[PDB]
Image 1 (cartoon, rainbow, N blue to C red):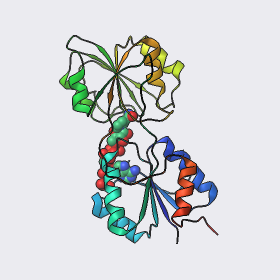
Image 2 (image 1 turned 90 degrees about the horizontal axis):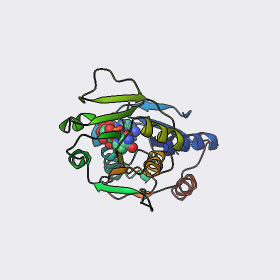
Image 3 (image 1 turned 135 degrees about the vertical axis):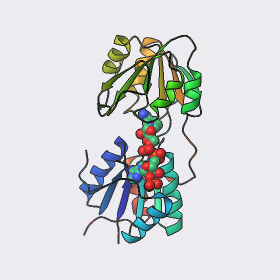
Image 4 (image 1 turned 120 degrees about the vertical axis):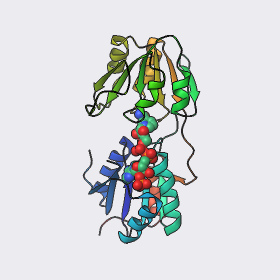
Amino acid sequence: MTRLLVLGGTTEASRLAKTLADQGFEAVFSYAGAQPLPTRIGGFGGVAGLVDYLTREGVSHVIDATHPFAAQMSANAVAACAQTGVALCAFERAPWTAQAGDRWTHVPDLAAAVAALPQAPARVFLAIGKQHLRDFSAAPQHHYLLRLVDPPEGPLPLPDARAVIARGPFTVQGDTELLRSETITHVVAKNAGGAGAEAKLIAARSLGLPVILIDRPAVPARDICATLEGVMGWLADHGATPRG
Ligand SMILES: NC(=O)c1ccc[n+]([C@@H]2O[C@H](COP(=O)([O-])OP(=O)(O)OC[C@H]3O[C@@H](n4cnc5c(N)ncnc54)[C@H](OP(=O)(O)O)[C@@H]3O)[C@@H](O)[C@H]2O)c1
């Protein structure tokens, strides 16, 4: 009968896991590498590996609550669920949209973000986690500010960088203090959507700073279950029921 796989990595995901556990769903949470469900860690081994997992574990439903920029995991979930007739929905918020006072430009990927930075040395907040920071070594004249969940193993791949180690979630006061104190001139961010990571954008607006926003990657179509209640509804509409 019902056995959920929740692909995590965000706050939508952690909150969702808590709700599922409260309601009594048989569910496993998964991270690539804050909630009480039994958690698997690490990749599945491509689409075939995920197919094998779904089949061996008798998964009935997948909820993809991965970050919107975890596009390989999302695309693999589409393919694997399609190959096994397992129901899938994505728990994702809509992208952020600009308002008055926002100074935003958009680029399609991380490479284009690097290319978008000015020639003259700037002070750039790379608000994009740990992945692919190296890419910015192709614009080595800038000062970079990083914010990382864990202390970096080795030396930063960036000629001039400072890493602040923190998780948050972050407040507008906090982010405005950071940007101000590091005299940031530009912010690079991914268009994640949601309230949880939006502080840095309000802070930027407050300080009158430009943001280079990386647009969401393309992922194949699947059902979208964009609030906790939407997820509960979709679960019931696909015959998922809790313990007992
Ligand atoms: N700071 C931001 O707001 C922001 C924006 C964009 C990206 N980033 C970071 O850069 C990231 C790209 O992330 P990513 O490497 O996690 O995504 P990914 O490129 O989609 O994942 C790469 C592989 O890791 C495994 N994987 C990912 N999520 C998993 C999960 N929940 N459970 C099991 N395996 C998982 C899968 O390997 P297998 O094929 O072997 O299953 C997947 O194909 C974004 O997720 C984000 O967190 C951050």
